[PDB]
Image: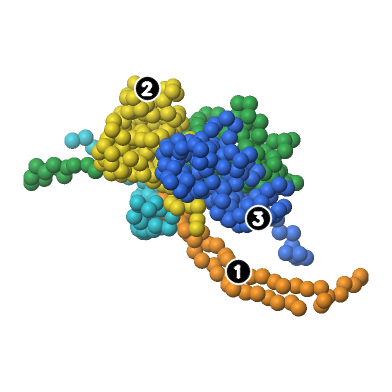
Chain colours: A orange, B cyan, C yellow, D blue, E green
Amino acid sequence: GFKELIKRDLTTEVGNADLSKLVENQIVGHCYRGAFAAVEENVQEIS
Amino acid sequence: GFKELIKRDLTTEVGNADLSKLVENQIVGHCYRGAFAAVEENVQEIS
Amino acid sequence: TRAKISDGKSVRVILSEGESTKTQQFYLINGFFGVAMQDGEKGDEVTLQIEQAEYETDNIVTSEAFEAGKLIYWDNTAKKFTTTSASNRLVGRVTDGKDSNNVIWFILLPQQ
Amino acid sequence: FKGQPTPSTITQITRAKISDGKSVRVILSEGESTKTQQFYLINGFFGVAMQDGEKGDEVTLQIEQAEYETDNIVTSEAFEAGKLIYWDNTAKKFTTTSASNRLVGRVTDGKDSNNVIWFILLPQQ
Amino acid sequence: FKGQPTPSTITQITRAKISDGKSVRVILSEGESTKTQQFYLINGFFGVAMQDGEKGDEVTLQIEQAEYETDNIVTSEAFEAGKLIYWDNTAKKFTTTSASNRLVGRVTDGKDSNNVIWFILLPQQ
């Protein structure tokens, strides 16, 4: 009942830079994911 | 008594990541540099 | 479809019968104050700059010191910048004060 | 690091710029709901909604200060190029009346036949 | 070109946009000082002093009109999302009261339990 949906696991692309400030490219991470949980599978306990 | 410090002689870069539509890719150059002068070495002549 | 159509750095206008603009000069046309990128004639289309950028100009009234930080107001009658703060329109703030050559660096403002 | 062997001190390097500010997330109120690519005034921020918000959820508004195309103008009034635009939060429409509305832009292209305006968004004051 | 062979004539092509203007150099007066990543109002410009300066030194202020994480507020006041932000230069703290203070921003994220705020910076009017 648990499914892991992935389109892009992870992508660290160098971002746009303001050359007029001599600021380096914005390192930015990006992931397109999702999950599908359920209740039929799981049972809670105490201690 | 004269030491020139060359960290980065010259580097020119060009980019149009987020510039205006009417502005072509602007060009920027920069250099890391430093110089140490002194009075231990100089004598000032006239004529 | 997208509401945003352009970055808004430049805006087009149509010259009236009492207006004429030359390249790279400041002109208040139809409520937009900016730097014209084309030499325009009556009833012609030109493009201004509203880039919120630092701008250089010497087209100032040379009577009062433009010390850094003071607001810059554009006087449409005399076609000059000034620090009068009268009914003239507000257009920017001085970044670098006036030099001996009467040159000003100032930041444009969002036309409110 | 939990259970580290030695009490290593931690020094925080200060930082101010958290984002570019092109857009802002906002929480929907009760009597509000947004569809994509339409202007709204939600918690004092005027901008283009980038997501379909229904109720009590989080949506992002675009405050880029760019040039925007928009319908939803009070067609009775005429919007010449250069006139200041105002937002009528009661009617949810653009107007030139400055009674108590929020100043939100200035027109670039005049009111055409299709009631379409091109205008420059303002700094959210 | 001094001593050129020929009397050539030089014609300048005008250029108004000296710089992008996202930041401004400023000189410290006597009663002013700065440290990195702290907000200040220096010579009519409000921004993030990216460098340390004490007396007659040069510092640069970020005026990008981006989103900024500040803290350093008047803790007694409440800062809901969307409320305007004013800089009280006498107390050197942010505040919502508009008595005689400079308007500098609008809160994007409300005052949390540790008095942290995210806000858009405004165009230095």
Q: Residue at x 30, y 43 (%)?
A: C45
Mark identifier at residue A32: 1
- The answer to whether residue E84 is left or right of residue C74 is right
Q: Marks 1 and 2: same chain? A: no
> Is D116 displayed left or right of D51 in the figure?
left
Asked if badges 2 and 3 are on one and the same chain, I answer no
In this image, E17 relative to D8: left or right? left
Q: Residue at x 49, y 36 (%)?
A: D77
Front residue of D62/C2: it is C2
Task: Determine if residue E70 is in view.
Answer: no
Percent x, y of residue C70: 45, 28
Q: CA distance from mark 3 to mark 1?
A: 20 Å
Q: Residue placed farthest to the right in the image?
A: A47
The percent position of residue A38, horizontal first and vertical second, equals 78, 73
Neighbor class of circle 1 (other Cα within 10 Å; few <14, some 14-19, many 20+) is few
Residue at left offset 34%, top offset 44%: C47
Q: Residue B17 or B39: which is nearer the viewer?
A: B17
> At label 1, which amino acid type do we have?
Tyr
Residue mark closest to the camera, 2 vs 3: 3
Q: Of discs 3 and 1, which sits in the foreground?
A: 3
In whole angstroms, how far apart are the C-alphas of marks 1 and 2? 59 Å
Name the residue type under label 3.
Answer: Gly
Which residue is rendered at x = 38% and y = 35% of the image?
C30
Point out residue C18 in the picture as x, y percentages from the top left corner. 29, 30
Task: Name the residue beneath numbered marker 2.
Answer: C64
In the rendered view, tell whether residue E37 sits above or below residue A40.
above
Label 3 Cα crowd, 10 Å radius (few <14 / some 14-19 / many 20+): some
Q: In which quadrant is the N terminus of chain D drawn?
A: bottom right
- Rounded to the nearest angstrom, the CA distance separating label 2 from label 3 is 54 Å
Chain under callout 2: C
Report whether mark 3 lies on the same chain as mark 1: no
Chain of the residue where label 1 is placed in the rendered structure: A
